[PDB]
Image (cartoon, coloured by chain):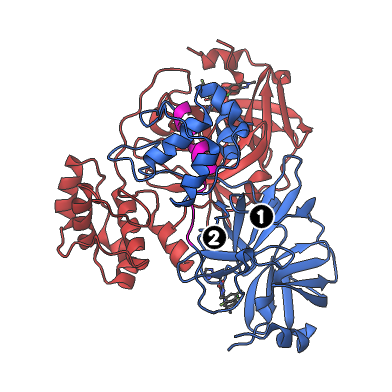
Chain colours: A red, B blue
Amino acid sequence: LKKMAQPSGCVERCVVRVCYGSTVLNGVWLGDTVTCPRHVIAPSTLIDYDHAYSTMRLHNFSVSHNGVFLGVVGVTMHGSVLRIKVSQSNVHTPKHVFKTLKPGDSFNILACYEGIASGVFGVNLRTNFTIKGSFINGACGSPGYNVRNDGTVEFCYLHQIELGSGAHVGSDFTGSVYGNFDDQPSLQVESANLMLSDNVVAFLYAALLNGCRWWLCSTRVNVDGFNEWAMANGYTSVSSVECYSILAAKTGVSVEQLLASIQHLHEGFGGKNILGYSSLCDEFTLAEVVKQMYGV
Amino acid sequence: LKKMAQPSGCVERCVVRVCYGSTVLNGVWLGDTVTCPRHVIAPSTLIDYDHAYSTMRLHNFSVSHNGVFLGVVGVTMHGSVLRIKVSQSNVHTPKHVFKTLKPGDSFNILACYEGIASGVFGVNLRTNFTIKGSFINGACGSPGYNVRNDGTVEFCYLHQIELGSGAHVGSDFTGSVYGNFDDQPSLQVESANLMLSDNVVAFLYAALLNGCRWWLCSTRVNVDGFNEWAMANGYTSVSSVECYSILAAKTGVSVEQLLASIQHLHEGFGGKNILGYSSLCDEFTLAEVVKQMYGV
Ligand SMILES: Cn1cnc(Cn2c(=O)nc(Nc3cc4cn(C)nc4cc3Cl)n(Cc3cc(F)c(F)cc3F)c2=O)n1
Ligand SMILES: Cn1cnc(Cn2c(=O)nc(Nc3cc4cn(C)nc4cc3Cl)n(Cc3cc(F)c(F)cc3F)c2=O)n1
């Protein structure tokens, strides 16, 4: 079990550099539209974006891909993003949709600087709607994506800000900020994360499939009992036993046995480890475990 | 800190599917040459590769890029790889070199199946010359690479085998197997992994720069003394001190203090953690720490 990213080639071909005056960040070029964070039009300064938008000048923009400049034709503002119409369509536009992530969803970040990709990594949207990425100044507008089995790219995230805690906040392509954080320099404090119980169950199945079984409780707790316990101990509710059927069928271990195991392991591993982890891991989804173990 | 891969697009355009008889793995297409593990010509049985090569027939090969089949013109064997000449050059061959890794080198893996990339991740060549990837059956031939600052791709790894431990072994593009394992289905056991001290020093500097300093020793241990201790305690030598000077200056902490700190912490943290880790982390190189925190 290793956190991986899906290959980045099809997304690299969509990253552009967006400049407005002296401010530079990343945008995503699809068809004849570049989407980027609206912070690119912020003054050097609480930002009044409505006023910055009303006094915008199109000739103040510079949009470029690999040093080649695209002609800017028009700009509209949608929530926390801009949609910049350009006079040229991206001939490497992949088959794509736009998807809004939910907590517990895994996705890929292509970390970009000045319109050029530098790194790719997998992340999980947490219950407080932040991610734990690695970004420095200039990463604003870095895209997050998933690639479906048929090849369709789901565009799901545009990087916005780093919180005081180090957590990372982005928007979707409609302009909604995940978690409704402000795209402003401010002292906002995210609420505390819960452990993603769905991912912990997937992790324990992966441990069973790698021979690691010292932790397995003999007895069971049902979903209703676990969910009552989860609410009192910083865990999310578990969603439907039936979705784990493939891993339950391959291990002979029911979800209820793992729910009971989580209750035990919450109080500590006691000098032992599970796949090299010293506490429970909610980093991997059921789909990731199934893909990495079986290719499905 | 996040382990990440460099963008994979330029390598994706070189991945091919190589088939000989019923055996299918991955290769890398550069110019008019495909390099792949020689296991593709193994019979279905201790493999006599010299005999398999002498009886090889070019018509048994099939080589394709994204489902487009390439004509096979000639084949030579070089150590544990084949060099397959095809009837056209890859028009997307990136500027590139071949480089043989040394233990402690980080690089990127593009995990491929049937000539199609499915995931990308960063790894470190360990002192026992294995890596800890995530690979299932069909990953043979998956390439490892690094991208230089000037854009030159260093091709450095072709995936070969998974040992009983789960550890992964590959070759370089000259055909030398890392660690001189055999490209045979025999039982082989790698030597004990040593903690990469250079990476642990980088990790402790990252902690200091993040305000985590509960563990810091005022004691100093010089390089020579640390290296003698390291021998007897599962650690590599520390290679040098001066490369850390930028981080030593920002923190006011000498490398020799961090060597003393490693000796203080090598058995465990008690109940405490460092950047979320419950034991010392050797995942991150100095270059990665400096790049991810300062963009250098
Ligand atoms: C450490 N870190 C991790 N993620 C981030 C994201 N991020 C960013 O990359 N850049 C930001 N400010 C800018 C400065 C610029 C200087 N030039 C020349 N051009 C610049 C462009 C930007 Cl966007 N910010 C700050 C920030 C970005 C916003 F979108 C926002 F609404 C409020 C903010 F305070 C930033 O967080 N940094
Ligand atoms: C679980 N895992 C992780 N990494 C690996 C690497 N690996 C591999 O992907 N495939 C292998 N055997 C093949 C079977 C095939 C069936 N078909 C239809 N085509 C096949 C092609 C291969 Cl290569 N092996 C085994 C292996 C591969 C070698 F290169 C070698 F020299 C000896 C070996 F025993 C394998 O390890 N599996």
In the figure, A41 relative to B286: above or below?
above
Nearer-N-terminus badge (1/2): 1
Q: Which mark is residue B128?
A: 2
In front of the other: B151 or B236: B236
* Image marks 1 and 2: residues in contact by CB distance under 8 Å: no
Name the quadrant of the N terminus of chain A: bottom left
Segment tinted magenta in the rendering: B192-209
Q: Is residue B269 magenta?
A: no
Chain under numbered label 1: B
Main SS of the magenta part reads helix
Q: Which picture quadrant has residue B212?
A: top left
Q: Which mark is residue B101?
A: 1
Q: Which picture quadrant has residue B239?
A: top right
Mark 1 secondary-structure assignment: loop
In front of the other: A208 or A64: A208
**Residue at 75% of width from left, 43% of height from top?**
B151
